[PDB]
Image: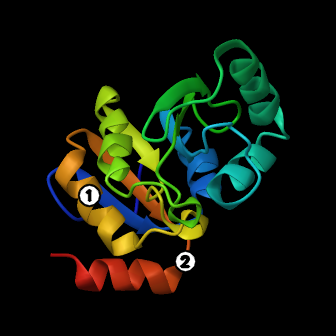
Amino acid sequence: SFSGYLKLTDNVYIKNADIVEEAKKVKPTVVVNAANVYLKHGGGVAGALNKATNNAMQVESDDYIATNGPLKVGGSCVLSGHNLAKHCLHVVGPNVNKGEDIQLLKSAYENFNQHEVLLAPLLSAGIFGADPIHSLRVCVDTVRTNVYLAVFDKNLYDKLVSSFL
């Protein structure tokens, strides 16, 4: 199970780790993907998770979109976790580089509450353009289930821990 995490609150844990490597090690019930509404897993966490599945995540996602259409910003869907996890919860945080409403970040984190425990990245961080310090604050103030946050960037991990209120 999860090891080497720093406890931030009753239910939020954080580690400087590559979420793909964490998923391969732990094989959690749920790994969260930082998805976009089209489930096009090109870059960031999504590109890395998809590449670790040998593109099986993308093939499955294209079938999901063909059947259901795009997700909403703030929404999610549960798909297979492939070799990484039992399930992948694809969650769409607002992409600030697309001018999406940052208030939808709370709605995005609410999807985590449908799962008792999750391995996840900070939503809307990285290439999604939001402030990761703000994303962590929204996470802690929204998610009530057990969330194990993997932050890839060491300098960002250090800044997140040292600034955590």
Tell me the residue at 61%/67% (across/down): 127
Tell me the residue at 53%/57% (across/down): 95
Horizontal relation, residue 27 to residue 115: left or right: right
Which of 133 and 96 lies nearest the eye of the viewer? 96
Kindly check if marks 1 and 2 are in contact, taking CB atoms under 8 A apart as contact: no
Name the spot of residue 3 as percent of width and height, x first. Answer: 41, 57
Horizontal relation, residue 12 to residue 165: left or right: right
Please, is residue 46 above or below residue 30 in the view?
Answer: below
- Name the N-terminal-most of marks 1 and 2: 1
Q: How is the image coloured?
A: rainbow
Please, is residue 145 above or below residue 124 in the view?
Answer: above
* Rendered-image quadrant of the C terminus: bottom left
Q: Amino acid at mark 2?
A: Asp
Marks 1 and 2, Cα distance to the nearest angstrom?
A: 19 Å
Tell me the residue at 57%/56% (across/down): 19
In what element is the residue under mark 2? loop
| Residue of label 1 | 138
Which of 118 and 165 lies nearest the eye of the viewer? 165
* Rendered-image quadrant of the N terminus: top left
Q: Amino acid at mark 1?
A: Val
Q: Residues within 10 Å of mark 1 (few under 14, many from 20)?
A: many
Indicate the quadrant where residue 8 lies.
bottom left
Name the spot of residue 99 as percent of width and height, x first. Answer: 51, 61
Query: Disc 1 or disc 2, which is closer to the eye?
Result: 1
Tell me the residue at 77%/52% (across/down): 42
| Residue of label 2 | 153
**How many callouts does the rendering have?**
2
In what element is the residue under mark 1? helix
Name the spot of residue 133 as percent of width and height, x first. Answer: 33, 74
Please, is residue 76 above or below residue 155 in the view?
Answer: above
